[PDB]
Image (cartoon, rainbow, N blue to C red; front, top):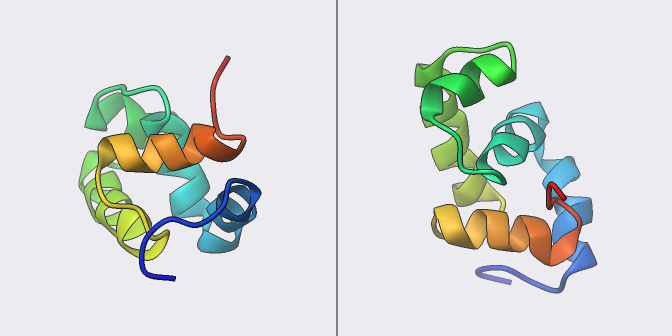
Length: 79
């Protein structure tokens, strides 16, 4: 239980995390700029910088790829 874990476990986790997670993640899932993201989730880029780094840090992620990967790995993949 150090990094990543199962597929659906991630999803259910993607939410248990917090708005900051479901927020930046759903923006990160695509790969848009820190600005469009922060604003895409009614917030500032300085926030996503905090949230994001937190999100991947608390969600058990590792990097941008890992996050989204864990995002799509479950159900956080924008078709």
